[PDB]
Structure formats: C-alpha cells, structure tokens
Length: 50
Length: 50
Image (cartoon, rainbow over all chains, first blue to last red):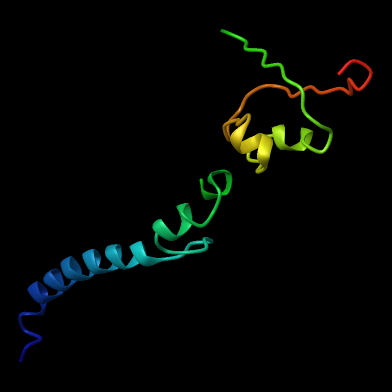
C-alpha cells in the first residue's frame, strides 16, 4: 500500500517539482523573442535589447 | 548639475542620426549618444555660412 507513506512522498515530490518548475520557467519566452540571452544581445540593438 | 553643449556641423540627411539609438556613419563612427540620453538636440540650416 504505497499510499500509506504518501504524507512524506508528497512532501518530497513538492520539494522536487518546486525546483523543477522553477528551472523550467528559466527556458520560457515571456513576450520575448528568445529564451536565451546570448541570442538577444547579439542579435538585437541595445535600445531594444534592454 | 552640469550641462555639456556639443557643437558640430553635419549634412541634412544626417540630423536624424543624432537621435539616441540611431545607426549610421555619423551615429557610429563620429558622434554616438547613449540609449538614456537626457537633453535636447538642436539643428538649423547654415548653408549660407558653411
């Protein structure tokens, strides 16, 4: 009955997914052109890159 | 606190390059202004003297 120890399994799963979701948002593209910064500063002008 | 008055002579089709963030021969290799320039750009035709 693996659901018996679900109290601590949920804790460790929330600790894991909180870090995995935080790092997954790093590769996001919120209203931008690229997710990485090297493809933005070296492709767009400073007035628009900022 | 302190005001700097830069003076020079350029052509007519080069006056637009004095604005911040512009690109051209005068903007890049002659006179560059930062993206956060604070001040006023003044230009008038001096064909009768220059």
